[PDB]
Image: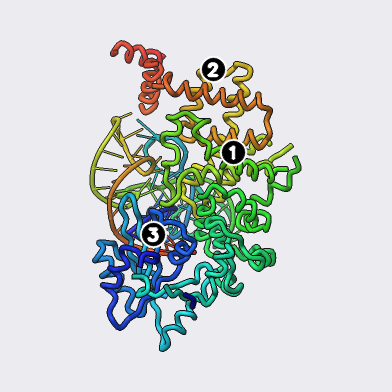
Amino acid sequence: XXXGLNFYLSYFDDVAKVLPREHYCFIVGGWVRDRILGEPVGYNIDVDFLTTADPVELAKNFAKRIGGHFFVFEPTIASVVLHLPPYRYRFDFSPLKGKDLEKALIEDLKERDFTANAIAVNLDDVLTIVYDPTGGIKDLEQGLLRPVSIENLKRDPVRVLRGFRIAIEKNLQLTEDFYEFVKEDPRIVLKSAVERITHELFKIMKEKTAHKVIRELYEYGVLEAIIPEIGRLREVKDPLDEHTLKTLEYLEQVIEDRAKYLSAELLENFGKKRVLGEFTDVELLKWGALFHDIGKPQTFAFYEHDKVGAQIVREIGERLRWGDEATEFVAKLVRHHLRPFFLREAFKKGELKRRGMANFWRECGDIAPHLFLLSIADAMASGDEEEDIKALMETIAELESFNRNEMKXXXXXXXXXXXXXXXXXXXXXXXXXXXXXXX
RNA sequence: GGCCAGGUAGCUCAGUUGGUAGAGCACUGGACUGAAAAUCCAGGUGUCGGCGGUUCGAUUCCGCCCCUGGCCA
């Protein structure tokens, strides 16, 4: 332990007004962390507490006070979730028990993954003596995220990704012992539950420096052990894997710059699609950039490798428990991923016509901007000539402007609607349709 | 409380733009054989989990709930 507006939160008062006299409560986890790091409070607040009283009644009355929902789940801990559009509050209360309070505190802290997460403070001193037996402060000053002990990483293998994510997110450098431990057994990641790996994988794709972490998870073979399919890109010598990596990185450089490639109506709904509740479609675009060609080593002489791509992606989505909607998204993104290049190649000959455009926007109108961005970043990774790229953005311009404006007996009904739609581009018309269909 | 997948005949499983719910096995009958196994032919009235919406028409499209399981880093 080393030496209120610095560690204040509005709701803390409420907790103290719930928490009984005899029992004591400590604030642990990422709150004290992010605060020490001096990063400002976001729109999503997550606070983990350690209390000596019954966390369930605590959480029930707390939630009753702030008008939050109540939660109990597996030790056995209690949650309170209060969610309105601008902000989200997750409070997780955890039990603490012992004949010696300080001893048990230190004993809990020491079991934690990283010194940056083991720093804790007493509730009373919030409303400035801190508890950091791992000495998290010292590392946080050096700007280094260092695991407490390797045994606690091995305990819950999924933490091995956290160490990457956190270090990228909070922008810190992992220590040597972490990277050494990953070099030892990169396969350990498979021992942890699947949806955790998925969820962490997405939490890494979320940020815009993600290409460096994905390269990292590749280079230690962790991204291989999770998804062996990525390991198979190297079995074909053009380099395919480096290609997918730089395509990813360029997809981030383009996505940040997205306003100046795509139109406004194409940016309108972009980013607005939700999957797994905290993640948008941008991460799906980054995934479909990683898998953009997953099928090339499967089929070569690469004729079918796009559909093969779709099938492999889909298998990865089923396996890793992604959304069926999201995995279908990524799979369709890898399926049509080569479409704008054929449209550009058709445009360079001036052979692109209303048919190709109408097909384009009927077949896939929703993945269009993602498809365009991905095609532009893949063109930038392939190192296309400037003229070729200019032609590409011009093609995109053509399609965009086409959609912009120029786009505004069971069998019998089907052909009736189809021919009515062809005519829109009258009982006598219906009778004539019937005569044309019957004859 | 959040996300995700399953719910279909007695059991267990197909059904990617919507167009009268099938297949295999099991069960029964018959042909065959001294007998049997084997082989061959024949037999689905299923409130597609429930209530609603869009369509001429919903297992599939959309909304709201029940139940089962997985996860909550």
Question: Which circle, 1 or 3, is nearer the viewer?
Answer: 3
Residue drawn at point x = 41 percent, y = 89 percent = A99
Q: Residues within 10 Å of mark 2 (few under 14, many from 20)?
A: few
Mark number displayed over residue A291: none
Residue drawn at point x = 61 percent, y = 60 percent = A173
Q: Secondary structure at mark 1?
A: helix
Disc 3 is attached to a residue of which chain?
Answer: A
Question: Which circle, 1 or 2, is nearer the viewer?
Answer: 2
Residue drawn at point x = 40 percent, y = 71 percent = A27
Q: Nearer the viewer, residue A24 or B5?
A: A24
Q: Secondary structure at mark 2?
A: loop
Residue labelled with disc 1: A307
Could you tell whether A191 is left or right of A297 in the image? Answer: left
Name the amino acid, label 2.
Lys
Residue labelled with disc 2: A353
Mark 1 vs mark 2: same chain? yes
Name the amino acid, label 1.
Lys
Mark 1 vs mark 3: same chain? yes
Q: Nearer the viewer, residue A398 or A62?
A: A62
Q: Nearer the viewer, residue A127 or A20?
A: A127
Q: What's the CA distance linking mark 3 and mark 2?
A: 52 Å
Residue drawn at point x = 38 percent, y = 20 percent = A421
What is the x, y in percent for residue A82? 31, 59
Q: Residues within 10 Å of mark 1 (few under 14, many from 20)?
A: some
Mark 3 vs mark 2: same chain? yes
Residue labelled with disc 3: A45
The mark nearer the N terminus, 1 or 2, is: 1
The mark nearer the N terminus, 3 or 2, is: 3
Q: What's the CA distance linking mark 1 and mark 2?
A: 25 Å
Q: Nearer the viewer, residue A121 or A169?
A: A121
Q: Is residue A104 above or below residue A177?
A: below
Disc 1 is attached to a residue of which chain?
Answer: A
